[PDB]
Length: 286
Ligand SMILES: NNC(=O)c1n[nH]c2ccccc12
Image 1: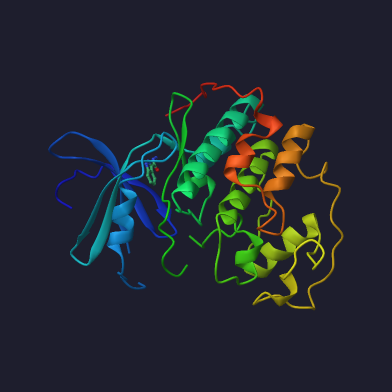
Image 2: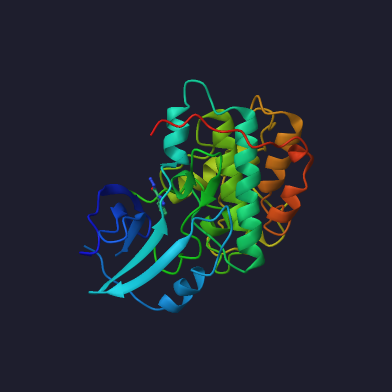
């Protein structure tokens, strides 16, 4: 509103645009997300308001929720860079494995926290992960997914969502995070689909077309078609080279087809991959 100087636009989320703004009175710098030629819905500001109570070092703090002038505004703590920009910036050299590991460990801590509070993200992507100069990484925009869906990015979507499941579980966030982990390691998106079917078939071509053996109930899913081509699962050491075996093992558990078999954030934190985890400082150019 008129409370801010609104320094500049900084991104377009699946649910709305975000702005860097300075409280024209307290001097506080924040990220202001405007929820909205489509339509301006409304249902539970109560739901979102509850999120203001989420407090964890790996969750971007939601400072306020404002419903006004036929618009919803979420005021968030501001972080200087998102992971998408950091990966692009680190494209020539790659993010050091210790930093990738630190970021994955922290993101799992944030998800373990949200999931233990029965809060799902549902739309995790590099643009939704924010980093600061001190080596922290935080998840932003949790629990928003309460409406329909730059073209939306399908790259991090769990297969059960693509197959039309009506009830999703915390497993969908683990899937997205696994996709992001792979991308930090290889410096290329794992499943860059350009449509829902292409997204699905890119997953099938790599992990093999799922069947009742690996995923009980898959053939009865809403959009499952017996006509799906049957691709054999790929080696996997071919998937995220040159990640070590602990990393590959953990990733494979985050990418299990059956959401019931997919590793939880809490269990992932105990994986051997994190035995030597540290907290490096990244080289951030702001
Ligand atoms: N460059 N900074 C950002 O994009 C940002 N900072 N805090 C957020 C909270 C939610 C969404 C984005 C953001």
